Image 1 (cartoon, one colour):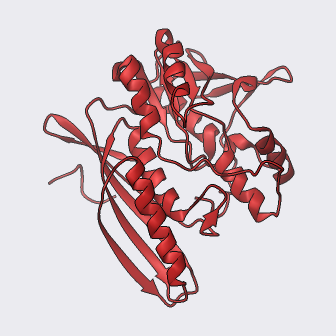
Image 2 (image 1 turned 90 degrees about the vertical axis):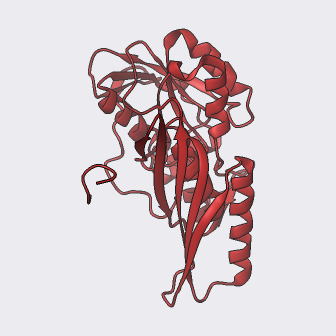
Length: 304
């Protein structure tokens, strides 16, 4: 009996004195290449980021690729090059893998599993009342950039995905304020920032009050989101972390992120409260307050 009960969100496994974090995620993004990245960089970044938000230093990645027989070898080579390069940015080795070819008329799916070691585990259940809620950068870039490209929407300054591994951003904060002062984190991928904040609120059993005006959103993302009819708070991010920090260390954490290249646009967007536990309240800039609810469904097709 090795686990947890046999049979059937990264998982944590206590291993003696330390903690092993184990995660897996499939990627079906189409097209395979998008502004700012590709399925290979996405596969590595998403796994590293899921490990990072649990406080785990990535130790190894495993990659499974399922390719259609009609795929051009050059496309495959470019994806592998990108995967290799992205893992080298962490750095974390891709220690094993598998490749299967199918006659099905697909191009490629990439599935990545990762293992990390968290000496000071962090989860979405540890937020405390009074804590500051931070995001490491602009919100909605990935999902909106891909949906925009799909619709032929284009801007003067190209709208690109933010896809990138951000273990370095998380480490920068921990090295400054100490892991003990990072109370919760979430990787705002599927269902975006709103889903991430609701998960922290419900799992930590705390309320979260967000000042809408403080959420960093690029002008192009705001515009494209209006054209697409979707909220940038509800789509996937692939180069960001949501972090809940002890109140007295909020500014230090913000400054630590802003000193990294990927955390340049970090911001404090709200605080944890003792009322409406399990809910996220949004103080709208137009004036007023409303609940920030995860998107009512329709997972944006093949963007991650």
